[PDB]
Length: 100
Length: 100
Length: 250
Length: 50
Image (cartoon, rainbow over all chains, first blue to last red; front, side):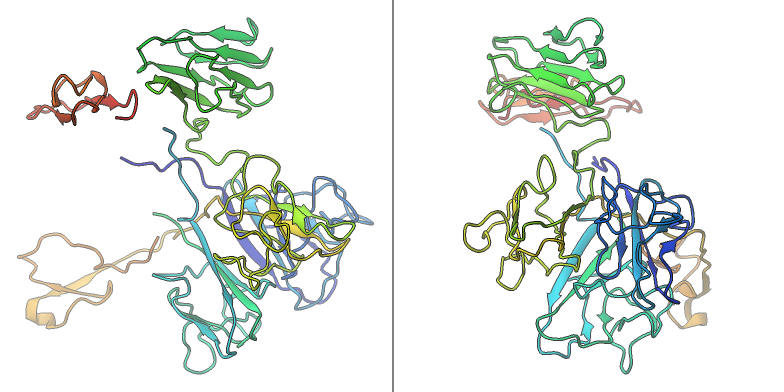
């Protein structure tokens, strides 16, 4: 009687209210497990630019904790950002994740 | 004859061009029934700050029809906004509501 | 049937296959001319996915079309399952690449993202939107890196987007494929586009609990309240409907 | 099954039915009383759209 069909991917949101300045990275993404890279989600309330197929200087993304510059590969857990942003300028990060 | 399942049931959204100033609240949110508090989108075309786990002065949201100030709990039916915003700028709400 | 054997199999009416394309592309042709039979379902499937990768090739050769043109329809869909019947209008209907993974949003991958770094200014129109297939007319993302204005149901000078390639202005319908943007934006100012799909996940409850207290008849004299108070004649009505307990829409 | 035979078809469970209503509407009258058996589909489908 019923078409329930296919599958539902999983989006959750966690807003990061920026403080203290600094804050060019955010760790563990959503506390449990990992971020799903393919769809980058981060906002200044300006929604931040692609991480992208090719990590670029154009793409503004730090990617986890790179020593200098910022890391060319993206990692799910930890992310970085090229910007200090500003306190009160909110880094608003989401994922499109496979499992909850 | 191929048959399809869909999204809109599990994802819908509505966006408001602001007029008249005032307009500190928005009633029923989307047409009928309940909004779901846990996931919030208010967009100024910037995506407005979290309502958050805690209704705060940081978190900018009115929440339903609060007589003075703006309400601490969030009813899915009615919402409010601390700001009147301005005419010509557009508030954009997006809901996340689960199917059974 | 194996990818190892041929690049082609054909025509076994009720003999179902679970297909490999790994070794070589399979070009599968189906019985021709089919007389007055119809009613005949054919079953092709993935016992694994070498669909995608090396593609399928499905063929209704001249004869009675699968659908429309009948030009060979090719499955690059990783999992897929095939049922087409010979159907009285000389037609073979197979259903929306159901992979298992049933129904479809195909290469859509449900909710998805693309960004246009805008260059040489201009570039107001943005062609083909997401790479293949269609965009989804349901909902929009487009961006200046600030969120764009709402698109609106009827397309207004207010609601800011072009909709495909209108020679002057914005196109009064919005086609999925091509999309226009009213601003040329700038080199370095990106346009960034999505439609909507996937639904969302609920995290629901994680336990909680309910308990009811009823007293009977006039002894309450009061009606049920939330999951706190209930009232009835206890001997009259067995069981409970529960709105009687506290209800919340998980 | 063809509409031309009966205006109604009846009752035979595990038999798939490719249906033609062109001649007349198919009134498909399925068995009643059925004991406790269940477990049994019937199959009707469109070989084409009548």
